[PDB]
Image (cartoon, rainbow, N blue to C red; front, side, top):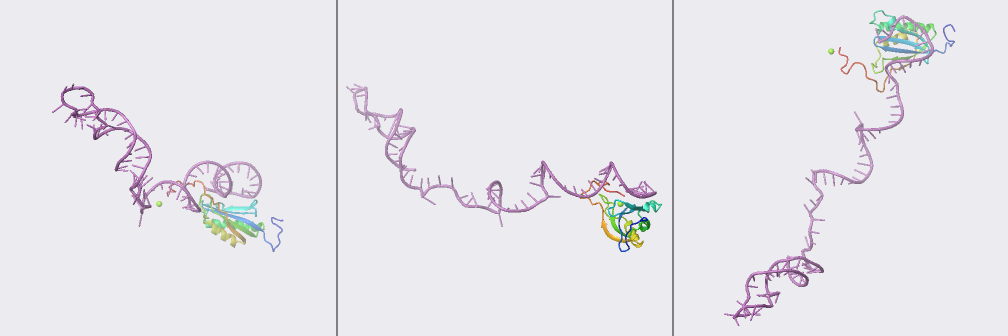
Length: 137
RNA sequence: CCGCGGUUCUAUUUUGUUGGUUUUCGGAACUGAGGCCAUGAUUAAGAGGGACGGCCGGGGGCAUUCGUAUUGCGCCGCUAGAG
Ligand SMILES: [Mg+2]
């Protein structure tokens, strides 16, 4: 009770932290083991007011700090990790904010379980956007 | 190839007293059974065709099945951002 479980000191409570780090944003999202219920979702957009640093490591660590204090306030100790890129037909590698957010989560008084990749990997995707001649910059 | 059976006509004769001439008279017409031919087919192209045996291949057509992804929808969660 009191915004927390009745777990003993010897046992730790396990959550699931989806880190959807794409380009131009970074989502850190803590849920239960099934993922049905969500505790807190913080993203770099609500921590930098520049519209350019949404995927910045400076904003990513701040977002991870907020979900860390919220998890500790809710009495959550151990936390699995599910790293996710944009996926689909689009880019399959995680954005810049993934490493800073993960480092912040470890150092801000949290425990780490298993790390897994939940990137959407198609067997063979649809027509990816851009044209056959690519994005001419 | 060689001989033997097997057909139709015809240059000439002088069986010079005319007549009839036998003129099979000479040869050329169609044919059946034989004998002999060492009897008669060059080989099978590092040419080809086809057959035969076990394979082999994202080769083709039809049918069937599977995969996550994308999009949308319907529920539940939490937040003011998302892109
Ligand atoms: Mg250029």
